[PDB]
Amino acid sequence: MKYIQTEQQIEVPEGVTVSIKSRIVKVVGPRGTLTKNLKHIDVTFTKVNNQLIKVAVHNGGRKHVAALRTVKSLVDNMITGVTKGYKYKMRYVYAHFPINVNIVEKDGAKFIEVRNFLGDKKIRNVPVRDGVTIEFSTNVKDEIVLSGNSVEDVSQNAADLQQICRVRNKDIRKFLDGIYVSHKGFITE
Amino acid sequence: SGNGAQGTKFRISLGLPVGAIMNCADNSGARNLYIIAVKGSGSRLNRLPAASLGDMVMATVKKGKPELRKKVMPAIVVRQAKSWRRRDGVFLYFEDNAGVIANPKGEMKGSAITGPVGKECADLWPRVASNSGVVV
Amino acid sequence: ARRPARCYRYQKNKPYPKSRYNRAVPDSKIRIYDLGKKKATVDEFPLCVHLVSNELEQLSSEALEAARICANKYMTTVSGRDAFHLRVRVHPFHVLRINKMLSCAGADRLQQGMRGAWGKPHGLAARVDIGQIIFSVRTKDSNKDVVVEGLRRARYKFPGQQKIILSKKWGFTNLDRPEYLKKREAGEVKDDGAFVKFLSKKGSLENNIREFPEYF
Amino acid sequence: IIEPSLKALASKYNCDKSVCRKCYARLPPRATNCRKRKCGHTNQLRPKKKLK
RNA sequence: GCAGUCAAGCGUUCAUAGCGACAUUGCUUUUUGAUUCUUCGAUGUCGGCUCUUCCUAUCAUACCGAAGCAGAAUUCGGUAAGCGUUGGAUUGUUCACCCACUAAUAGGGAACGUGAGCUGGGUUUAGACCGUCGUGAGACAGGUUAGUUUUACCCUACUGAU
Ligand SMILES: [Zn+2]
């Protein structure tokens, strides 16, 4: 039933600093600074070393032990986007009507717009999330490479363009037009 | 509703409801046009649907040329006698209710139209405008 | 009119079969209570599985027929007719009656109400108690993965919870497997038509030498 | 133009899916139970019929 | 009437896009029963008009999923009762049935909503005719005509007013 002890270990890379007090994880490193708040989990961190953090739990059930290894992976995605970073290559697919994507800075921030998506006359606004720079691949005419130091604000922004460029009232297996993600790489690789 | 109408017409005072009878204007042998319903015609309980100047009504012939009697045909009304307001201010009304037989697509079955034809009708259907002697 | 099966599910009234006092009874919807390799010896099929019941209620005649069909259009398609001995164990012997009052039912404009409520027979039923084999299937041991599935498909055609139990007896007999090994080692047991005849140590002596030539 | 690798990419989100038989909900291709509480996480699934 | 269950077979291929035979478990109370608990010092018994509100088992509209969904067109399914769901010929009709419009002409409750609100066409007194039945008086959930619709000023409710 309730497992008496369940531990995981977060290997902390070189040059990377981690600051934890009352389940708030501030990570600084060679590029970027990430602060994720974890008050919703009963989890005890402990500094067993300067190179690796032990994360443990006590008397947890199957529900709670399952929500322990999701904590190690969330810190591991924090330090990985802080050492290397994250970049998402996205790709334009269209049958006839070309998609024309730009970047505009309106009153608030860098809205992303698409125009002529399947011949449509309505622009499709989608804001950037901050910490994410927006990049176009110059060599390939139909490509877009999102990038940033958090995997969350990139991938939510990468799924934002997938959600906004959908089809309506047609066969999706015939009308396979849209802006899909193909590659989820790191920045320094 | 009015399939084949070119653009939009405004609100003209509904002067001739169902059961009305218009003297047919064209020379296609009909004389009366007993309105049985109108294209348009929103639904409210015990309200019988009414037609105005320029609507397409569905009408049966009650007098003349037995080729056309005893069946249903669409008709375009070209004169009404209920005084309606033009948006430039003036109120006006013709001296008889009158209607012109047509198909659904607006092709008037006749060849010409006697009497005057209201501007609100002649502007809406092109083939009642290419057959009208006097546009008011 | 086919009145639903939840109307004649429980055992409310006492048994009432066809008799000399029940001359006008229609027949059942079952006519063949045994299909498969009916002309098979006891020796070829050493495994028997039982489809027993968990409650005390009545089994309809067309219900058992439709489940007899469903078990038999499974094992004949995935294992063929040769490799099962299906034997429907329970017989529809009860008679279910119905109180008809239809708008032209034997009588005048209005038939009656609950006056003279005795009803003419319309259907048969098969009474099954708590633990009573319904579908005994005899086949080989290594072909048992079909009859677990095949009688699982028969379970959905009649109400109640019905267990699928395998039996340690040598097929359709009433004695275990290790007894039948020693009774096949020694020649004590002699093959009948689709059953088998056992040794009677009690009896006339010469009839136990007129029979059993292999023993002694 | 086609770029037939991109049609393999576009099928990952539209054609390489599975549908539940009870609630008709679109599901992963490697599903085992439906992710809803209306069918009841049923284990009666089906693949998505493709084109032609 | 409304659904669930298992799947032989239909769908030229293909048990389930859609159906589904043989069987089986249910729900609903808008049908019809069956019963006789309440009402015989009377609860005004059909239908229509008027009017409000509620239900979801969704006809339309909104946003979605699914297919023998290329588009159009059409079918199936989910959240959803917010909002709409008509004009007429015939019949006393509920019901039916056509004509026509419409986005659509969905199904039901509320003492089979609603008569000190109406109407009285129907049925259900007395007049009278016909048909059959009866020797006869008379009979007929058979046909056809003519047949008085009473009271609120009290309490509550509601609408306004001090
Ligand atoms: Zn599902």
Image (cartoon, rainbow, N blue to C red):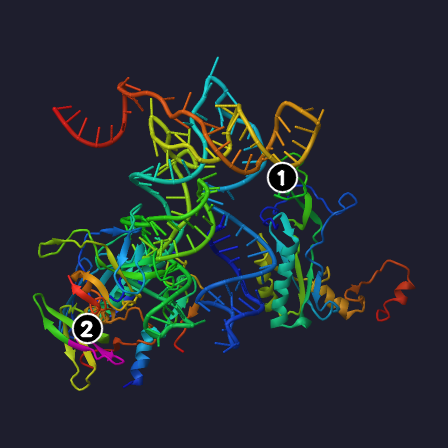
Residue A39 seen by the camera: yes
Establish if E71 lies above or below E58.
Answer: below
The number of numbered discs placed on residues in the rendered structure image is 2
Where does the magenta region start and end?
A81-101
Q: Amino acid at mark 1?
A: Arg
- Is the residue marked by circle 2 packed among few (<14), some (14-19), or many (20+) residues within 10 Å? many
Q: Which residue is mark 1?
A: C109
Give coordinates of residue E26: x percent, y percent.
50, 48
Residue drawn at the location 40% of the way across and 78% of the way down: D52
For label 1, count other residues whose C-alpha is less than 10 Å away and answer few (under 14), some (14-19) or many (20+): few
Tell me, yes or no, whether the highlighted magenta stretch contains residue C148. Answer: no
What's the amino acid at mark 2? Answer: Gly
**Which element carries disc 1, helix, strand or loop?**
loop
Image quadrant, ligand 1: bottom left
The answer as to whether the residues below labels 1 and 2 share one chain is no
The residue nearer to you, when weighing B27 against C126, is: B27
Taking the image as shown, residue A97 lies to the left or right of residue C30, namely left
Seen at 27% across and 55% down, the residue is: B22
Q: Residue furthest left?
A: A107
Q: Which residue is mark 2?
A: A81
Q: Are marks 1 and 2 in contact (CB under 8 Å)?
A: no
Q: Position of residue B123 (x, y in %)?
A: 18, 65
The foreground one among E20 and B93 is B93
**Split into 4 quadrants, where in the image is the C terminus of chain B?**
bottom left
Q: CA distance from mark 1 to mark 2?
A: 89 Å
Residue C130: x and y in percent read 63, 49
Chain bearing tag 2 is: A
Q: Residue furthest right?
A: C206
Give me the chain letter of mark 1.
C
